[PDB]
Length: 393
Image 1: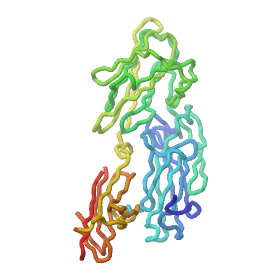
Image 2: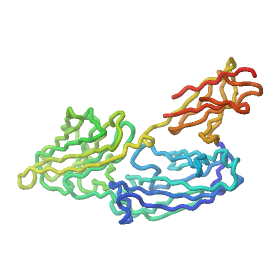
Image 3: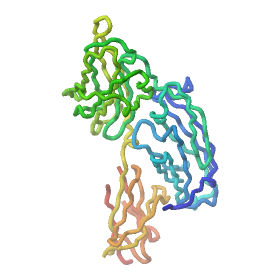
Image 4: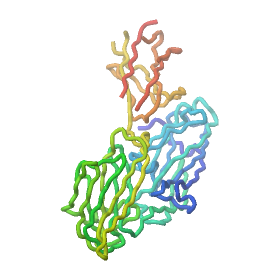
């Protein structure tokens, strides 16, 4: 069921891409040098659009909003003064963001603006370095396509590693061993990091390649078709690091898929490195290493919050209109109290909201304010209980 109608045909938009990161100079998204695809949308909305109406952004087959951090989300659209024009929600199943217009469009005419999204490719689709992909998206029912070259910087070296993705609890770390296919003995791999911790060998899996084609450049390999080691010699060190003992591998190539835990209340730059120590072709000890850094963006890692409460007559107050507002007074959502006088709003992005309780004619409450039969309370979400007692005037 819908809050409004599909108004793609009523939203007139122009879209463009900007390559960000360390690969700007090369016209490539450098996936290991902070690279990302920025999508910029300038838009006009027809005056016939009302609150609840929505337009869509279909991200197509190759990219998704957000970058390295899951779950993926889109932001609400605002005007120059921070008033919410549309609520943003993302569905991962269809790879589509929907923007539901607020009562802004009913207050203002000639609604104009622009918003931007940071995007990343699907590493299972965009697999190869220097691969030029037709990044085709649909904005307000209108297709936009531009070729974008992606590069992960996969080298035929003893050791290279990358962070596949990051969640609030863990990251997936991909380590490639002996892509150069040199004769190696006494091969040991050490996995360590800042903001990360290993607690069990269960969060590390070891795979053996049949040939170099299984070394996917995107560092998100096809694990279902890789040969997993049944007996991986894994030891969890006291410092929180882990050591994978591959043994005498010869010319064999290995993939290590690890899931290090995030440290609670960690702030700053997360680091994951793989240290590969071994004995080479000519019986000499060698050590190679590679490190990956990642920003712990809290707002892009936090799930979703919500709040609720009871409304009563100082007896439960049923069917009282409760509006969810942004701090500027724009309505984001509406509800009513149930038979027990309970209301709630869930799946809200972190930040500040206003709760508006609509008073029945001739009723008053009892910081908080009361204006023209409307009791407004401030709420911060990072649950929370907000109640309202009703008294006769």
